[PDB]
Image (cartoon, coloured by chain):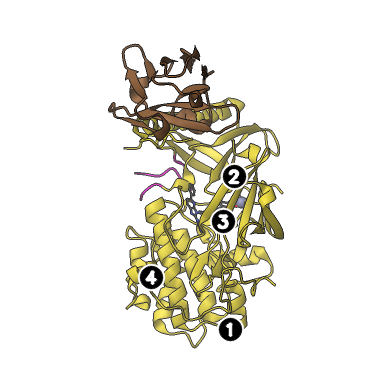
Amino acid sequence: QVQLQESGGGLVQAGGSLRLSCAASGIDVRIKTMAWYRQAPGKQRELLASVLVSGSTNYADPVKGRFTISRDNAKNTVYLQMNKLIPDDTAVYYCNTYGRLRRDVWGPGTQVTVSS
Amino acid sequence: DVAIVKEGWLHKRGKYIKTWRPRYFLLKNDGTFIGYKERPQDEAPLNNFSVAQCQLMKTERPRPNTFIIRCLQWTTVIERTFHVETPEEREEWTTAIQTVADGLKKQEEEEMDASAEHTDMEVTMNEFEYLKLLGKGTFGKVILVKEKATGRYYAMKILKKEVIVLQNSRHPFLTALKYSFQTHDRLCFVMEYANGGELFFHLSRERVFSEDRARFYGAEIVSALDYLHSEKNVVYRDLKLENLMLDKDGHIKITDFGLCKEGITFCGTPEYLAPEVLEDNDYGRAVDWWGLGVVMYEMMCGRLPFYNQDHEKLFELILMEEIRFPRTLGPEAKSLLSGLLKKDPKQRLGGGSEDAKEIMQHRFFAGIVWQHVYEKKLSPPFKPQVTSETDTRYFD
Ligand SMILES: *Cc1ccc(CCNCc2ccc(-n3c(-c4cccnc4N)nc4ccc(-c5ccccc5)nc43)cc2)cc1O
Ligand SMILES: [Zn+2]
């Protein structure tokens, strides 16, 4: 249909790494600012990283230097490489476009759990 | 270039007089949907006429094959109602309109999606004291409220959510939107409320304003309408004495408390209605300069230029009767007012390509520095009797 699908979550030890991918069908990721988000069991949803159409990236502070957002135009997918994971990273992760974000349309998200 | 997507005759429901009038409508690809007395031959398009973001109802009362465009315009829900002869005609029109609207949302979303710049970041009724009903419309009400945490006063416009589903204006004499929030069934706009009193009350007590006092208020109004016309491409269509308040320092505030009343009493106030609005003609920026003329005549003369307790005869006065002036009014005032109150919008002061500049150059405003007006650098002729923002001298 018209939707984003997140994948790549699971259980992982602290200090480890995880690569999340957001596959877009019916949406072209080349034409849209893309962003990753996360939401934990009790807190607000958090902007994490964005990549503009130009390729320029931007990171919120508790993630800068450990995560990198990248977009691969060929397979119509954004990525979030997550390195040096801290249990404060445990949350469900979502990717989105600006238009869907203001309309509060979200894909299913993927759960990332880090504890040890 | 804006090309015609569909054109043809429709019956437009009238608000003031003839109830059902045939008009020739053009639906254009920029979203404008505009009806004319006759099919036209050949100014900047007004957002008042846009179908963008509208919802479209088909209906069969009070006429068969009627349809409705409903739009939220800033903080006001408005409904335009139309009738065609055959249901197949109505489907051609609703479909053409939806297709134009959808194409507008589409290109817009793709453009903002492409240009979002780490603007991809992710209040309740309980927080307010109801004080006093300010107005009721078909789809909402406007109430004076007190924000509990701060003690400050606001007007809150409360709309029915299901008839609808940072952008503020930098003009000092318009009503600023403070917050916007929603409940499960309502959309609420919280907007500033001036506490310097209502100008209708001040005028009533003073009986008349001097030409110099009216010049100050008129200048501020002209500067606000110029801003709406040329920065927002909207006409106000609601200028009347009761929609003018003063703030704590004596500067004008034009209120945004209006609600359409079609389907609950006229919508506006009949004695301020421009001729082309009465006849449901094609109107543009010039309707506001008519409103300016009625308001300033009232300010400088102590009474309306047209009045009759029978609204049918008032409409006739507005459409037909030439304007008479009190014997004491000066000629620059008279020149201004009769130019603003020309019945033909094409002849009206401000009704030409230049718009507000025509009024700003009129010799009645000679010496006004329009930059100092916008920056509130002119000294108010009247300082209302309040010395704080939370002073309720002029409600209680
Ligand atoms: C039958 C019928 C028709 C129309 C109405 C409502 C008439 N217009 C009321 C109106 C129009 C514009 C605005 N407005 C303001 C404004 C005006 C005065 C004071 N403060 C403020 N803020 N500012 C804006 C910005 C944008 C727009 C806008 C309009 C149309 C489409 C898109 C944007 N409008 C305003 C306020 C009130 C009633 C009726 O019964
Ligand atoms: Zn109305």
Estimate the spatial distance between the alpha carbons at disc 4 and disc 1, rounded to whole Å: 24 Å
Residue B365 falls left or right of residue B47: left
Which mark's residue is nearer the viewer, 3 or 4? 3
Are the residues flagged by discs 3 and 1 from a single subunit?
yes
Residue drawn at the location 60% of the way across and 56% of the way down: B258
| Amino acid type assigned to the residue bearing label 4 in the image | Val
Mark 3 to mark 4 CA distance (whole Å): 23 Å
First reached walking from the N terminus: tag 2 or tag 3: 2
For mark 1, does the 10 Å Cα neighbourhood hold few (<14), some (14 to 19), or many (20 or more) residues? few
Query: Which three-letter amino acid code belongs to the residue tagged 1?
Result: Glu
Which is closer to the viewer, label 2 or label 1?
2
Considering only order in the chain, which callout, 1 or 3, is on the residue closer to the N terminus?
3
- The residue under label 3 is B191
Disc 2 vs disc 1: Cβ atoms closer than 8 Å?
A: no
Distance from label 2 to label 4 (Cα)? 33 Å
Q: Amino acid at mark 3?
A: Met
Judge from the rendering whether residue B199 lies leftward or rightward of residue B285; answer left or right. right
Q: Check disc 3 and report its element: helix, strand or loop.
A: strand
Question: Foreground residue, A21 or B15?
Answer: A21
Residue type marked 2: Phe
